[PDB]
Amino acid sequence: SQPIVFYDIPSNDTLKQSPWSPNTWKIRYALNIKGIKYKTEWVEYPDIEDVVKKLGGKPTGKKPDGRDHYTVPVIYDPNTKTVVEDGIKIAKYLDDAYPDTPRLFPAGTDAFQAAFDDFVWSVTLAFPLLSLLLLDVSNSLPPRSSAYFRATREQQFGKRLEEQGGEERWQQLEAGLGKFKGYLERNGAGNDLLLMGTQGGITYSDVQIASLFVWAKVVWGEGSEKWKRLMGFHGGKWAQFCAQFAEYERAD
Amino acid sequence: SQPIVFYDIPSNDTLKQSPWSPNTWKIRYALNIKGIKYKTEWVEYPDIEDVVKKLGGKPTGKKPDGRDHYTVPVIYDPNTKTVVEDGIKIAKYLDDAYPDTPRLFPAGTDAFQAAFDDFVWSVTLAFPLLSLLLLDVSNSLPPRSSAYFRATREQQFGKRLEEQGGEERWQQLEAGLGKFKGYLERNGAGNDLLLMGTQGGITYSDVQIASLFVWAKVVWGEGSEKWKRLMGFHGGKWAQFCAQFAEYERAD
Image (tube, rainbow over all chains, first blue to last red; front, side, top):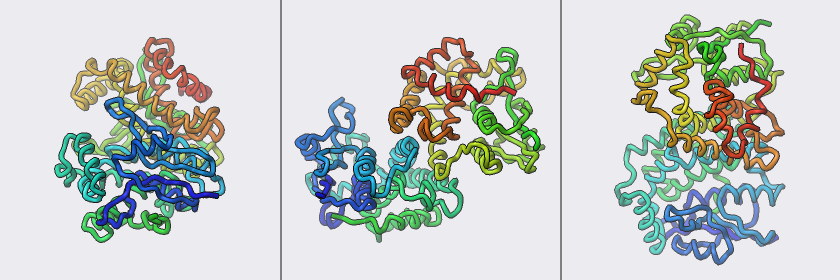
């Protein structure tokens, strides 16, 4: 059985070309947790539209110009001759097409995890963290990608990148992560480190959060002041949380 | 074994004193689905804080004045001499203390359902519908409660009640309800009428939506233009959704 081709966006020498994207990382984690064979195909931001089209992939949405929006993660599975785009579809595909690998969407959790998906990618939690990372990401891309990144994101938010971030958002972040700590604590003590209990296994929804963190960790650097601050939060719960995902970090 | 005392806010003769609140209804449903014996204690909006204090209950949050905020639903269980406040705590309590009754929080769904809670009570879905009901609710209350309701809610949003609502919100409502339809549809055909599939049973999270709808139905009236419009949405999916809850409507 052949390796799955996995399209990821690369980084420059300041990150040792470690993968960084919180969106592709949720599928890298999927692959690693599931132990399915894959090889990374690196693609630059400006080249994603053409690469995914030439590949026969579908766009994951529309831009405000009504123009097709093509994104990564994306996968080509030789073993089934299919091309899956859109991270939460790709993860379920890895469930359906490889049923003897750990299930990221346990039975009946399918709609709950979809709801949780809107919680993550929202002004509550991912966007604050984005703002803290928008600039450092620009400086962590190869030149062509970095240029595309700065242009498009600056347009997207009306600000320069250097205007983004600051303490207003470090609070919003702590607040969102707090809300999440809240939800987890409803699982009761001893179960407050995975959405379905530190008993009933890792889910895609867990992986989504793990991915926000690994993204921060890679771009700021395990030693940075920013990373250590974030691990500061909530008595270091997120340190304990991220540890569960340590064995699943295989940059390739 | 003795009836649970269940505090709900009453309505005037225009609703035949049917209970109406979408917050108390989710616990009414819980009790009816679980077939646990209860009797309703009616309490007026302005008398809630004192009733719950004289009862030994805790407030469920803070007002912006930092002043304690006491709310219903609330229950007193004679059989265990305890007083639970806060809807989602009350529902879990009815799980824990009555384990041979249908479980509203199936194992490991605890945090997922807590995340869903924030989905429901948000500008996405519950608030748009609130704006469509704020006025008719005020006209549906006993005079003392109606007065308190109009006062406090007008202060809360900075508009008169009569300024609230309109098409802008009927769209937001259709949109949020669409987003729900989307989540459900991830369960696959034949499973898209309950969060855990029309197979794996009714959850508290399901009940929360059913309660928004019964609220609308009671206040507007099963015959109203508004109610029929709402049932119009998404090809009448919500009609099908609501039917699952019909046998659990016991005003008392």
